[PDB]
Amino acid sequence: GDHPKYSDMIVAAIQAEKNRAGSSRQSIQKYIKSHYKVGENADSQIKLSIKRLVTTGVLKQTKGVGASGSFRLAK
Image (cartoon, rainbow, N blue to C red):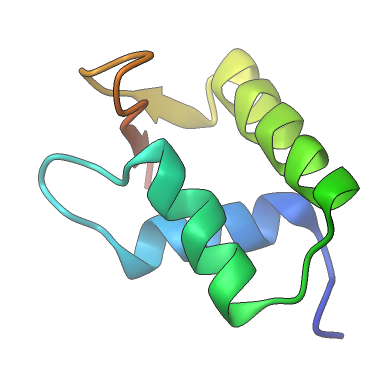
């Protein structure tokens, strides 16, 4: 129950830091790693899931792409 869906954790991380500038890419994994136990493989999956979410358009794109990789949550 502490590890339901990667997207849910990503959403939770972004919701936790619903900053105007958006949530940094590092912040998404940092929040998840800090609040949820993750492994190296999981980190890779998180990055893939974040990318997929952006790909599906679920996650909004924010500036600093590649630098910070800020992402916004489309409510």
